[PDB]
Image (cartoon, rainbow over all chains, first blue to last red; front, side, top):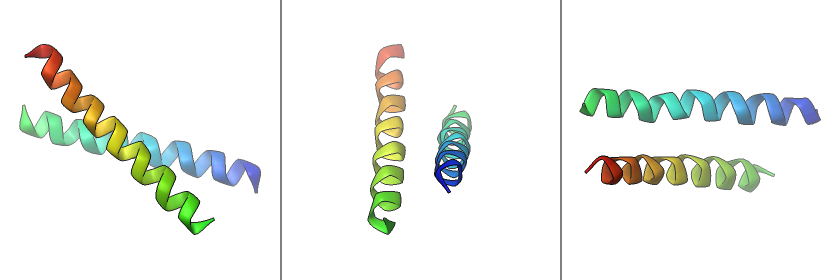
Length: 28
Length: 28
């Protein structure tokens, strides 16, 4: 259960970081 | 706990998106 939160919080943040980067790359 | 997930994800995406705005500003 502790590792659930860590694993989903980090994973979700990583994809989200790339979602923004994709938008940047898209904007570039 | 739902509010935790909402607040942490919103704060995380918004702070990193405004950091990307900072990067645009830095390149500018």
